Amino acid sequence: RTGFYTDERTFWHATGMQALFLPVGDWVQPPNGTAGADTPDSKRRLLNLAHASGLIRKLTLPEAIPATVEDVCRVHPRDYIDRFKATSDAGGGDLGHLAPFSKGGYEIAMLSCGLAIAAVDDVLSGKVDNAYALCRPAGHHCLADTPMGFCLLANIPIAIEAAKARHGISRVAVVDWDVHHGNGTQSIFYDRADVLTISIHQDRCFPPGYSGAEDRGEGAGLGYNLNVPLPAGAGHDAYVQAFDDIVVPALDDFKPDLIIVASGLDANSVDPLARMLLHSESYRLLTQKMLDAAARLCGGKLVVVHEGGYAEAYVPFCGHALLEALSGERTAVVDPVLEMAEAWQPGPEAAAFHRQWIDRLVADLG
Amino acid sequence: RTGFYTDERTFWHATGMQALFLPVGDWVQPPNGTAGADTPDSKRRLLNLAHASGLIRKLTLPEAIPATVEDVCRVHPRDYIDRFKATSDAGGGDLGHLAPFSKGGYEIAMLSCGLAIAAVDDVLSGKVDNAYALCRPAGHHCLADTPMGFCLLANIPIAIEAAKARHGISRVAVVDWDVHHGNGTQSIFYDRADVLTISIHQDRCFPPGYSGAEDRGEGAGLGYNLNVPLPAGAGHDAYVQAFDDIVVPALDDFKPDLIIVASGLDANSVDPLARMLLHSESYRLLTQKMLDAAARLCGGKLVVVHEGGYAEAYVPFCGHALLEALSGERTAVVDPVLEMAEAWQPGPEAAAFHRQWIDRLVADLG
Amino acid sequence: RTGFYTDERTFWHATGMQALFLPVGDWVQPPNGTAGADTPDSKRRLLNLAHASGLIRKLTLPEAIPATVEDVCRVHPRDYIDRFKATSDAGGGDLGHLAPFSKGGYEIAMLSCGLAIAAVDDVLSGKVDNAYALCRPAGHHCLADTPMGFCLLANIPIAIEAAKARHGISRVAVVDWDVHHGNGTQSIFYDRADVLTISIHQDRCFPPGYSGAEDRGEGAGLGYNLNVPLPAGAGHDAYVQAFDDIVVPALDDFKPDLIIVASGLDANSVDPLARMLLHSESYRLLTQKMLDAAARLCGGKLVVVHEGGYAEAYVPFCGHALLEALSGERTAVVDPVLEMAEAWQPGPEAAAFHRQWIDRLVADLG
Amino acid sequence: RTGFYTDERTFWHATGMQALFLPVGDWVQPPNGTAGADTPDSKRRLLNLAHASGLIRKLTLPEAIPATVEDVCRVHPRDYIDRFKATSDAGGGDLGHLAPFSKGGYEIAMLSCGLAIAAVDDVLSGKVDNAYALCRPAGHHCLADTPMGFCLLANIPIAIEAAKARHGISRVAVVDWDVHHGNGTQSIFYDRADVLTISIHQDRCFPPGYSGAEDRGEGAGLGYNLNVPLPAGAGHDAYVQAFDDIVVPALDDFKPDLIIVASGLDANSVDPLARMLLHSESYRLLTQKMLDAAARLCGGKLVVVHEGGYAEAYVPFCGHALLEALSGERTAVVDPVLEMAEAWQPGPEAAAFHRQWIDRLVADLG
Ligand SMILES: O=C(CCCCCCC(=O)Nc1ccccc1)NO
Ligand SMILES: O=C(CCCCCCC(=O)Nc1ccccc1)NO
Ligand SMILES: CCCCCCCC(=O)O
Ligand SMILES: CCCCCCCC(=O)O
Ligand SMILES: [K+]
Ligand SMILES: [K+]
Ligand SMILES: [K+]
Ligand SMILES: [K+]
Ligand SMILES: [Zn+2]
Ligand SMILES: [Zn+2]
Ligand SMILES: [Zn+2]
Ligand SMILES: [Zn+2]
């Protein structure tokens, strides 16, 4: 059984008047359509398609339980949380780097975080075999005291520290396949060996200029952070090989008691915020690889937490195939972009380059 | 002096109710924002920024002259033009492959085509040194009998045939740096040596699966078509080397009497419809290379014709830098994405791959 | 217990590329925002608010069962249904007057109709005490052979004829407070005494020019149709008096076995498609009058069926107060427009005119 | 010769993240389409249609020159101007009641104001016979120290005080047919006899609850302010009579040297922000009454200044007929809503009430 953790009010968070990610003003003309990049529909349309296909009726949807302040302050200093609340009450703002929010965004962020907490809690309790948390706002860029890149709270780290306090879990692996670097997760556990943090991301995209393969942790955490930068334009076969040659072997060696996927859908082939070429069947297969790892390593315990994804028209098909895999349910959904996205895939010269790139990352892991 | 060819009604063309490029229906939910991918604002926002900067007041803007049926039938069979008009009167439709239009789309396509005809005409007659035509709908995928990929009339080929009839021009080169393959231009002049057709495009993107480096023309046109596919994820340095090592030498060898650029802006770093990493200063520099080529080979005679470009927030900055180069004008516009897009650029390993790719294209040309 | 009948796919119906209700083309520029007037969000935002307030958790939400062909053919000729299905399969169209739809609109209309059928069926069988059907597309303008005014099937009449076939109910009253005339309901039952059809509507609005107070039925149906036109600019007190002096006495005289409210929310104070001045507490009060009537006349059997409503920002508050009344529940929702809409209400001179108007309608009823 | 005063950057002002006029947060869900009520397109679409019809080519369009600090401080205290600029430099805000703006909103307000200043200046200097200023943001609610109701500077009063300085003009009449009360204009000149301020508006609409027929000025201004409240639901014949029986006689008695119309188009039949029933031919006729008055009283000197208007689909046709009248030009534009709006007009009983209402206003004027 699969739990699906969602709440209407996560779709009411609004980043404000931006054209894509550009703040209005100076030379940036206001948009005439939907404002922003992290739009409500770039996440709701996934849920909409899961309703329309009949898939949601196969899942269990618990009522949302917001994070408490005690929950979030296992990661964040209370001063940040207090300033967040005060700014949110006053009409919204931005307390970090590219992390805007509107009035009431504090309550919505606390709610979104609670979806991740409860998804992990219910999987560890045996209430469901696995779970999907449709978080919005996302979490994986948020530092302990600095929100960034549309992330206002560290959703997954907070869910992990709650699981440690409630269940005493020893080892957790986070597999971050959102197309951007999970710098928040990396930072929060950088000197710890009990959380393996893996990030696969477009080389140099966000944070801009960052690659990170050499950043493997510090102190007790040395060897427990793993960055897999991939070149812009990499597609299905590049991601499959990175998972076969790097990600899955890392999980096997670490022996986690729980696997958490930070699942952004923005490596899809038409996303504006990156340059990758994944399609809906890429996400099905990557999910199947994680289902296999969780079955082999930690009794099936697998939690998928929504992060990025900005192509409103194509994110739903990528997320829906993921959910079909997670739940083991077949529906009648047909991805109308798949044939073209398969034709888009890199040819042999690019494929050789991607294979050589991943071989080098493996060799450098020693 | 730069002429700028535009008309309000080009922004009234509407592709219909699609989510991005996906027709609504079946599993595709209707969009709540702007419908379509070729949206009015993905072109109008370029014009808006050039007004706001003061650039437009330095250009000359002739009143638009629509193409006549006689003009367009120098390329298209009258039967296609007649069916286009009848379908447009009847409420719109799609007479080709991914070329939808609404009621009245026939008249707007004829108007758009007339912007290209007149821009070429005015440069050849000496009224302006160079020109930019803000065509919408675009033209470079349209075959003689089949519209395709948002292109309903073969804008540049029709403008070329009109210039041959009115001015007797002998040799024309078309430099197509829209991110997609200019298959319409290639097809229409494929057996002809009087028009050199060059397309730089994302490998396998649109038409899907097509690369085309070996397709060099046929009969008298053998050696007068030149495809430069580039891998997904290529950016500024790759395009610059492609122009220095392939495009500009091809122009030098051909000795054109007029250079026409098919300028789509969809190779920009955040376009949803391709995977490339150009930024606004890429377009400025590529335009300077074309201005230099025209100055050396054909008395400065250079026409730039708008094609694709789908990132509403970033296309304006790319086109504005292009227009500053074309006109030689300075404004106070600053691209707020430029620093980040510079950081996004491919690192050393990908750069070596791009150089190996272009070196192979050069070697294959003999 | 209140049943709430909704299905995700009702929000996927799309009227097409119109600016408000105006088809694109000729002098109508395409919209840059949401296309259309009957937008998905003009109905979904009511459901969104009911989720956010916690009210949906207090209701029972049965799974949708679409109308069958047998159901809809109790009202519509099979030829209409077949041409609708064939046009829908082929990409959508408009088979009547201002009733456009997209590919697959047939199945969505059959589903929307099933919400009304099930709401009536479940109230008559005692599964719920009363019910709300969030129909989209709406039904009350649809004639037996002709769709019109955004209405593709005659939702309420189909649900009535189904109820007669499955429960043998003798007398049904329809109270239509959508701001436009329920010409479809009026036509379908015009010569019948077993369905009392009451419409309160803005004088001359839609169908344009129609008032209708003298159209009281024909044959056996003479005295069983009741039109209550109200002048543009009428508000809360005018509607309340119309219900106290005309609508409720007609219900009392008729002795229905079931009351169905055709509930459009477009008499609200900021609707673009009418000129009325109702606010959220108007809808609470009018709903309470129908609850009281149903308690007194037919054992509490009350069904409310969504029709029109076009102000996306204010329809939610009006419908939410209606749902609070229907379910007898209170939430923390506060209407932020209420104070201003109360200040907007007609003053003493206009109020005297409205009383004079309603008194004339009463006197004419003999 | 008609001057048309417009600048691209007036369409870049953005009120922010509101659903219609409701700020997001608490119970107001963010919009998925265009944010706000005063949207860019609610004004630009009028300009767009005037381009498409060919009418703009018949007008003279001078380059905009913004208001100076000296210009605006003839009306506003320097402290307000300084706080406006500081807030705008720092990201936007709202310094009054329902007057939000974005970053750089100060420069755009100064530019908008300069359009009105120049339109008045050029008519008085004889450069054009009459003029239309497409102001955005609007002006007529702004008080000397408090912005209000989407108005950030007192556009028309600033233009008048500039005309007194530059031309020494003695008497100006302002005729405000925006559907809301021109409380800014009324307040600024309330004790002055050299400016006659007339406002026709929906009774009690905005400012909410205000009617004002008894507020006729104070001191030297007693008799030089004239409020004409009209009931909600009034249409063409009611406005025509108000102008024949009240407005034009007031102009004839006052003997102005210049007539300025504060032209909001929000009395149109489908505006969300009022309940009136004007159509495009109403605005043509009211403009002709003002042209006739200016020719009779002040040598043709007539300036029309855009204020409100929120129906994006219908405002263009209303303003376009206004511009045809003002310029004395005919185009091929046909209003596709006209026939329906004519059928919507009040019937005989409502028409008698409107006539009695206006007779009463006249009687109270003594
Ligand atoms: O040159 C061009 C044309 C770009 C076309 C982009 C590809 C869109 C496409 O192929 N869409 C589609 C695919 C399958 C089914 C429906 C639509 N734009 O600048
Ligand atoms: O002249 C004008 C101003 C119209 C302003 C109408 C806005 C309505 C309003 O005041 N709304 C509101 C009230 C309280 C809280 C939030 C919004 N427009 O043309
Ligand atoms: C490209 C500029 C901003 C990108 C933010 C990325 C957030 C995410 O991880 O989805
Ligand atoms: C053009 C104004 C009215 C159009 C049809 C409205 C249908 C309804 O909601 O009843
Ligand atoms: K990642
Ligand atoms: K190309
Ligand atoms: K009605
Ligand atoms: K007014
Ligand atoms: Zn991301
Ligand atoms: Zn293209
Ligand atoms: Zn209605
Ligand atoms: Zn107004």
Image (cartoon, coloured by chain):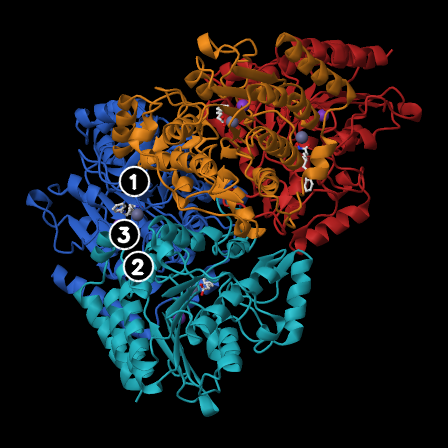
Chain colours: A orange, B red, C cyan, D blue
Tell me the quarter of the picture where residue D301 sits: top left
Query: Left or right: B347 with respect to D288?
Result: right
- Which element is circle 2 on? helix
Q: Is mark 1 within 8 Å of ligand 2?
A: yes
Query: Left or right: D129 with respect to C157?
Result: left
Kindly identify which chain the residue marked by label 2 belongs to: C
Amino acid type at mark 3: Asp
Res. A102 visible in picture: yes
Q: Mark 2 vs mark 3: which is more N-terminal?
A: 2
Query: Can you give x and y, in whole percent of width and height, for residue A260 in the image?
Result: 51, 29
Amino acid type at mark 1: Phe
Query: Can you give x and y, in whole percent of width and height, for residue D320 in the image?
Result: 45, 48
Given this view, does label 2 or label 3 mark the residue nearer the observer? 2
Pointers 2 and 3 within a single chain:
yes
Q: Name the residue carrying label 1.
A: D150
Name of the residue lying farthest toward the bottom: C219
Give the Cα separation between the discs numbered 1 and 3: 22 Å
Give the Cα separation between the discs numbered 2 and 3: 9 Å
Q: Name the residue carrying label 2.
A: C321
Which one is nearer the viewer's eye here, D158 or C123? Answer: C123
Name of the residue lying farthest toward the right: B219
Which one is nearer the viewer's eye here, C47 or D284? Answer: C47
Pointers 2 and 1 within a single chain:
no
Q: Are marks 1 and 3 in contact (CB under 8 Å)?
A: no
Q: Is mark 2 within 8 Å of ligand 2?
A: no
- Which element is circle 3 on? loop
